[PDB]
Length: 209
Ligand SMILES: CNC(=S)N[C@@H]1C[C@@H]2CC[C@H]1C2
Image (cartoon, rainbow, N blue to C red; front, side, top):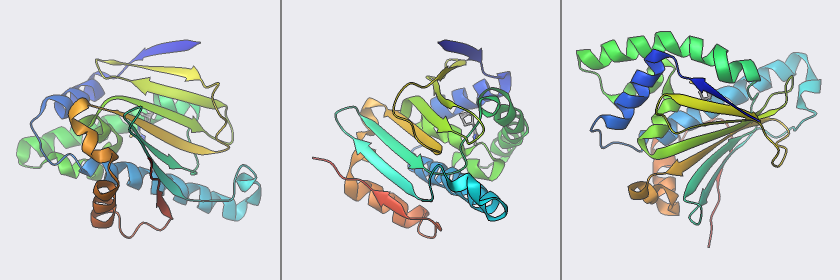
């Protein structure tokens, strides 16, 4: 079922800093998640050039933004390369240790949280607006997995039994109560056009009721 892991001490520090620091420019989280999505889409497109079989799990390379007001969730779906089990628990956390160390020294020097992406740890800016983050992912060499955390120093991983994704990553943001503005269409449009206008993949914004 569900395995529980401790964050590395430095990543827990980062999440606590992002969660507790007073910083009003929260909308930068979307640019970071979209940029992470566009990087995962580049990687699968480059790999499929020398091996077209990597696209049997889906030829489309796009990003979907799905707001859900009934669940108070904002979901970022990309059909990129996805992540394996070792990526969730070990590989990506080892890379993020040096980026997090460099990010804290830059913050002590006068930098601000909006520059989190320049240090490779941009995903954690989801905790500017989310009380809990679910990450569903499927890589060609592994099974589908669900990653989840509410900060507090721990995260969980389980094998996902939901709808199969084919290939890619789905980030579900369970928004905090005062951040429901990022479920509105005109608001998401404003943030995309301002921060992600030149992404080289179709960004389709879903609408609701
Ligand atoms: C680019 N990915 C980063 S920065 N982090 C990883 C994504 C998932 C959440 C934490 C790990 C697993």
